[PDB]
Amino acid sequence: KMEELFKKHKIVAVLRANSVEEAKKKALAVFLGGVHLIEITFTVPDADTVIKELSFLKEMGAIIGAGTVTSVEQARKAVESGAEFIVSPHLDEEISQFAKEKGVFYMPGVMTPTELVKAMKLGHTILKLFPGEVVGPQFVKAMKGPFPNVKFVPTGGVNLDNVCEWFKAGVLAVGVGSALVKGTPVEVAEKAKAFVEKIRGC
Amino acid sequence: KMEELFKKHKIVAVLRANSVEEAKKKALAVFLGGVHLIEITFTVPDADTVIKELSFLKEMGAIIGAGTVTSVEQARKAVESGAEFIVSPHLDEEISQFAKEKGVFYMPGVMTPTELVKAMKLGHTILKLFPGEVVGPQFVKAMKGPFPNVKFVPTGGVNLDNVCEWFKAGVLAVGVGSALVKGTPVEVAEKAKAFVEKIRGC
Amino acid sequence: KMEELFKKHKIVAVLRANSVEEAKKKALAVFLGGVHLIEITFTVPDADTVIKELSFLKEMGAIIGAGTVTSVEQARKAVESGAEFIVSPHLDEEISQFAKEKGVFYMPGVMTPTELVKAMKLGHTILKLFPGEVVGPQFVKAMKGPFPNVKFVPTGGVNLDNVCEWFKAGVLAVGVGSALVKGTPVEVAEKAKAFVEKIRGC
Amino acid sequence: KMEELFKKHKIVAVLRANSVEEAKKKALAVFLGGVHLIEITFTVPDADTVIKELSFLKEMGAIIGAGTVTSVEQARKAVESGAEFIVSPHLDEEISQFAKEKGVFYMPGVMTPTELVKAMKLGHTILKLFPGEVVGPQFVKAMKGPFPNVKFVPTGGVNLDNVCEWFKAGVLAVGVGSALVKGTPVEVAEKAKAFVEKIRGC
């Protein structure tokens, strides 16, 4: 199901913000603009409260998860507050195990073939590729040779000009932060619309 | 001896293909065009059978190995079928150990200084650099400072325009996949000739 | 204090050389040109002797450390000879632990989010980013999102044209090798002056 | 079956070479370029060994025979080493008889109506016409009148410019030597491709 949602929606908003209020307003902006997968990063102050207060959007079909999860303690709080998926920038064995026992989808981040293989050995085949702007689509295309059955969701620098190249390389979905989320609510809602159209357009 | 063969031939064909028949025809094409080091990747269906059926080319001086080796079970099959060398995209401690006991040359893939150091601690000084198109010659030149005695064989994006830059950076040999191997047998045999000449030419 | 010195001086000369004499002359050149943080790499022959013979420059305010430290045995020699800080290209748990017990500042090198997190778990928040020319400022900016409290000192390709971009990305200091250190003593002393001015200039 | 293979493939490479190694490389070149009928002439040194060492290509669908067979002793060695067909430049009653008892297809060479008739009396209706460059398509057309049921495979001078004229005259297949086989492996593989296309093209 987690796989199937990424496949269908193709875009996850990676939401960094300086306050609970800003984070909630941007999550609403993004949703109102057609982005259903919303990742509340743990760099947001009181990121758990934000996830809990957005729980109602689930009734409107939003899928609210947590990102920048770097300890099992953070993972527990996110899940306790209703996170439907966990994302980290790195591969965390302890978070992998906790999410396995808890029955919650975890997408670890990877930047190398060795990291990729370790993640596969922990049962993962959908991987966050981070930072995407450093490795690029080139990395995604290179992995298709030896690891035809791994799929990536790049985060980092994905924007309006390159989103289609990423999909050409073979990515499953993209995670979009500052290109989507930075600015005012109005600007964010609008940029949300543009990304959906640009993605549909390819 | 394994080192010395890489040093002498300078190019390894990294052979991905959709069938046994295609893989064998491309391995013959490449050999006929002057490429003696042939890596049958385990993304080739029945890659073991292909290695076994190419065993006779060893009598003509071909050196047939296996690539995209990701488990010890695959490693065992490759060696059982006559592989003279094992290559992986990542650093695998279990494959390192098996190849050590079996007395077969293993070239793990590495993308970072930490991975490099771990591989050295496992006894390796000839490393696959993968994906070469992501890190580049720049990475090879950067490693010369702190690790003067490590040598790289980059795989990923090596082509006719950049092969000489790679050798300028200090690589021991190059692994060439799609630029060499994609196309028909005739086109592959011809591209094989071009790479040998271009490499000799630098 | 180690943090505070990096913060104040902003540049560390990464000194590779073919002899004790060349290394000492270049360390003097660099210091005479205004660079106070001097990293004697262990690729310098008898790098310990060089650190010991430069010990007097500490009385003039030079801070002499060791780089390219790849084993605890090398780490011990460097510290025994008066190294005030230890730098490696990779993350080394054994060197981390030794430096912790010995009470000496260690800056491990990292290239990925997973490596970064492991280093943080070992108590490090100032990280060498290596090779900087492969990942770039882009990597430093990407890390600010999920890891706002990590600071980088990139080594690899930092030069007169890009030093200000690096500081724009949010680095704590830069480690400069060949752009600073290559050439004759006179040329090195002069390039030292240029880097200090260019850094002040941004 | 022998008839039917000639009919289907339309071209037999007549392989003369100065060594075992050259002969094998050219047979591979030709096969890789789409020529399935390969005639190893007995002017090749150790022509039997070459036929035996190419025996595996039979598993890839190559049909390996012997040419320039001029005694029953040579015929025996060729058959013993796996030759699937025997070709001679002349009509040899002794080779005809041996091949009849052994159950192996023999194509004797003929240049005159009297030779043709003698071959028919020995049970042959598929004849090598040799030397084709001396008699020409004219000879093939002339034979259609009195001997409508004889079919020729000309050897001698068949090339890219005249191959279609030969087929216009009514030949069953062509045997191509120097126009196909002379040059390096790469050049031979390529010329092989050209002949197949030119033949298909008519």
Image (cartoon, coloured by chain):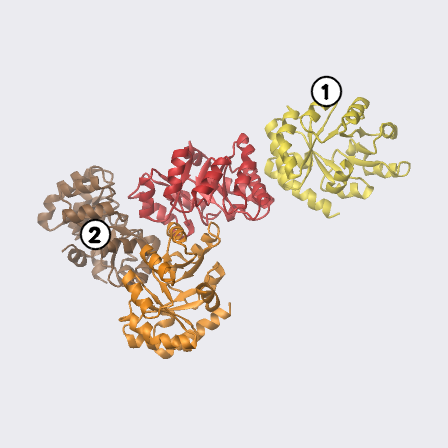
Chain colours: A orange, B red, C brown, D yellow
Foreground residue among C1 and A82: A82
Give the answer, above or below, for where A69 lies relative to D61: below
Q: Position of residue C131 (x, y in %)?
A: 31, 51
Foreground residue among C40 and C192: C40
Foreground residue among D6 and A150: A150
Left or right of residue B129, residue C95 in this image: left
Can you identify the residue that label 2 sits on? C12
Question: Which element type, helix, strand or loop, lies under badge 2?
Answer: strand
Q: Is residue C60 visible?
A: yes
Which chain is mark 2 on? C
Which residue is farthest right?
D146
Q: Quadrant of the N terminus of chain D?
A: top right
Nearer to us of marks 1 and 2 is: 1
Q: Is residue B10 visible?
A: no
Left or right of residue D201, residue B186 in this image: left
Question: Which element type, helix, strand or loop, lies under badge 1?
Answer: helix
Which amino acid, mark 1?
Glu
Foreground residue among B72 and C149: B72
Q: Position of residue A125 (x, y in %)?
A: 43, 56
Q: Position of residue B63 (x, y in %)?
A: 49, 35
| Distance between mark 1 and mark 2 Cα atoms | 83 Å
Total number of numbered labels? 2
Give the answer, above or below, for where B16 lies relative to C8: above
Which chain is mark 1 on? D
Which residue is farthest left?
C59
The image quadrant of residue D2 is top right
Can you identify the residue that label 1 sits on? D73
Which residue is farthest bottom?
A186
> Which residue is found at the position 45% from the left and 53% from the top?
A143
Q: Position of residue C85 (x, y in %)?
A: 17, 49
Which amino acid, mark 2?
Val
